[PDB]
Amino acid sequence: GVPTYGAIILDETLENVLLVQGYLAKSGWGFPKGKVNKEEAPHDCAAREVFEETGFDIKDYICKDDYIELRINDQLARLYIIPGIPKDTKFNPKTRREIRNIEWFSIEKLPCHRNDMTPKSKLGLAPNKFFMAIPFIRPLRDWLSRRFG
Ligand SMILES: c1csc(-c2ncc[nH]2)c1
Image (cartoon, rainbow, N blue to C red; front, side, top):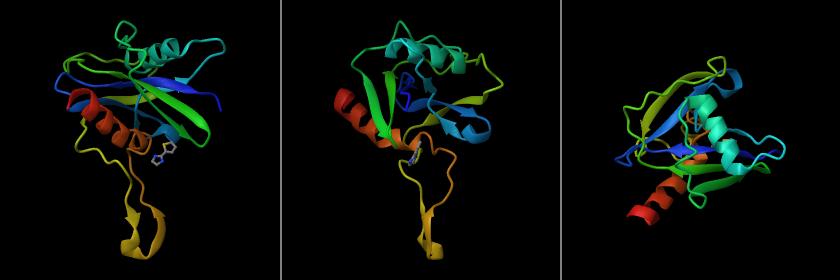
């Protein structure tokens, strides 16, 4: 799989994160990210995808060692951590044919797993509009604990 790169953008209080909503297969809410181009450097892919999806330029704020990286079905996804972006920042995507909406969400209110259906004696998980974000929520909480207490 081609690796993906993007960002976890937080506000000044460290309470809230920035999610984007796409269309169709990407119909729920997720962190802004995308596939790396041939010969493009990881920090440059992250800034590019985040600028296309949100209109905000992170290049001056990336810290090369501050990220969370997960492998999901043998595809690597890395999101650079970008704290202290004011909640009154105007975000506007390039690509409104790809992005429906852009919003701030409370970190403590986001799920870090989906719910089962063991009320109904049925296997699997119930749908959740935060599917794409879920896998990063517990590692982000643990990384904020370590770096800021
Ligand atoms: C693939 C992309 S996100 C994802 C996931 N979210 C929650 C559990 N697995 C799998």
